[PDB]
Image (tube, rainbow over the protein chains, first blue to last red):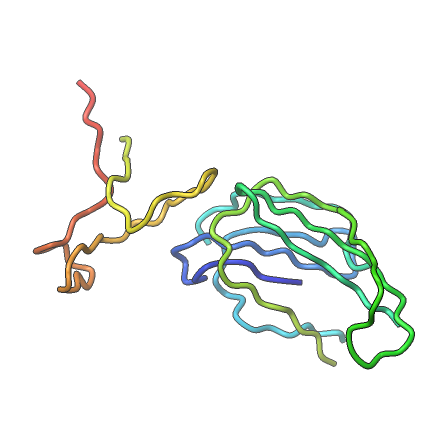
Length: 116
Length: 49
């Protein structure tokens, strides 16, 4: 998953799309506790909340993210690469899956980690 | 009971929200959380009568 925001110090707004193995994946609320976590594999107010299907169902995946007029458009595609050396040639068009209705001041984004 | 913002550094993008309250500074001298000289509160009341 990816943590979208501007400063994350309880002043600007932040977005908290996260993907897990359960059915309920997305939980978007204003928080500042999450700086750099890793998964154990064994504040203020919530402006908008949304729950849907998990998103990341030779396994090259490609995602592009857009921010047009406060709307968060997400496109995705799965590409079965054969030789894993660098970015392969050819074409593979990405497809829309989930369109969020709101997002304010997305400036910096993070990436999550999972360790054993 | 109603507040509006009249002080900001830049213009607002369409369909955006700004609920943060900080003391605005329009000069070289820093406010440092004190509403003294060259320090203005962006939240002002309507005052309906």
